Amino acid sequence: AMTQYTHIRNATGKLTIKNTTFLIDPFLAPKDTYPGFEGTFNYQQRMPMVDLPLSMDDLLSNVTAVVVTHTHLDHWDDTAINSIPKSLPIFVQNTADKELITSQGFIDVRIIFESLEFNGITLRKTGGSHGTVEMYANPVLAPLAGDAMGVIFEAADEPTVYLVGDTVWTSDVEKALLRFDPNVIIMNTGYAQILGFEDSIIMGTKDIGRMVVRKPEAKIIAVHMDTVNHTATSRKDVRKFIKGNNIESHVAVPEDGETITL
Amino acid sequence: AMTQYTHIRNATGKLTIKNTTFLIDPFLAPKDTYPGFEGTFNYQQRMPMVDLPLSMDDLLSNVTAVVVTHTHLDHWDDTAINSIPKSLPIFVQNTADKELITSQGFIDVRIIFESLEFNGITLRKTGGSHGTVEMYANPVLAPLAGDAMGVIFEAADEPTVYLVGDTVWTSDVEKALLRFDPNVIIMNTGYAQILGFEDSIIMGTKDIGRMVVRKPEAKIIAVHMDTVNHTATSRKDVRKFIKGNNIESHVAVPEDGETITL
Ligand SMILES: [Zn+2]
Ligand SMILES: [Zn+2]
Ligand SMILES: [Zn+2]
Ligand SMILES: [Zn+2]
Image 1 (cartoon, each protein chain N blue to C red):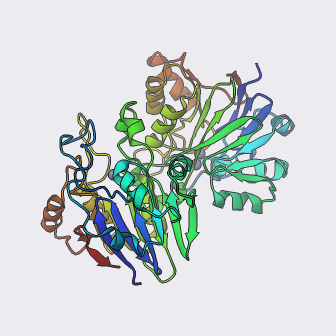
Image 2 (cartoon, rainbow over the protein chains, first blue to last red):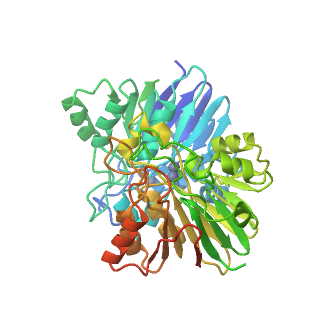
Image 3 (cartoon, rainbow over the protein chains, first blue to last red):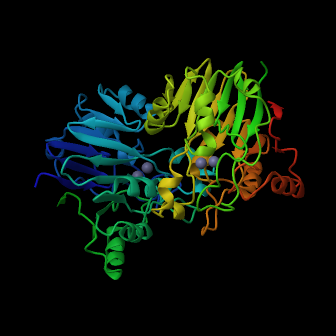
């Protein structure tokens, strides 16, 4: 009933658990507000490539708190800064992000050092690498990639939800999966790519297949697609993959604005 | 007094910086106190295989604080628990380790969530994975491997020291190297291995070579050898490797009890 995930756009969503609704990674700009990311796949394309699926009023209505996994543009933007009430609790990954968001007028910013409790819900920070080892060995790409957390949400009699975040598949993902055994796994599978590099700074179809093997009973939700310029894996791509591998019952690919009951 | 690293045994060492001496990962048991780690390379061999190189006094007399990267036996043992003054500040990686060590009678235990300051020195936690991704996907091995931090030590007009810790080469290592540009890099290079698995839960000669490539100007110090049963790479092995690659000037392999001026 109450517990649900409403996908908004890219990695932006609203996760409701009990009476608490978390606005996740709000990148709220109108269509084509920005040029494509410099030096990335398909940089000529402006972003976001689609408008939000609902009015700002409907988007913000029942939001209790905000979770910001990192402050890359496509997870935290000027539109969000100027639209979200400054008094809402904002959960962030580290002091640098807290300082940034505080400087933007938010008066209740909370760093998840390990875990925090909020209205009976436990939020646990998970690790991640926003790129491969080779990419982090590159002095130009590395600082642009930075840190980006995932979050485990736990609450009594509710599914444990793993917001994996902007990471490739590392041992931090294996750690979270085994330690917390999430029942719902929200994955960024747009396979964002950089010019001159073969792999991705986030996940793609390979990771979806691997997740189904690791957690055969979990409800997987694939997002972070069809919005920014450099995500080389689309919803259409993921749909073909999950169909061909007979894993459609395991993996949801929600449309912008679509709600999935958890 | 002067900034230096005195190696003790395995990963145990004393780092003196800004007139402050840190005892690192104290595993202080007498020779052959323990059977070899179960299920590991060369498990028949008891450990530690040699006695300490100095008295407990020479070891503990000038210690200002203790740094415990994780609580595996070969980094924190009963001898350390029973000999280290209970009032010494102990720096640890997380709440679980603080709870364990406080339960062992230590009354000043400090979790490095991000960084902490002590006596004018900044200690920054670095990430790591004590095994490959494949190892962490194995539900038997993973909990035995656990979390283990590295530490960056910084102080005004002193060399930045990177205690890499029990990790294989991951993006967390690349992150630390680029963000903090350490001048001294202490690596665990014993290449500990598990029966039935090809790779290692820590580093080895391949990592030493790679570290020299990444940081040709840094003083590398290779440790974590010739003590526990499962470290498949010895001091002899490392010395052959660095000689053969013409990189001896970059890599120190201190004996137990040996002091290196930094
Ligand atoms: Zn990102
Ligand atoms: Zn992103
Ligand atoms: Zn260890
Ligand atoms: Zn070890």
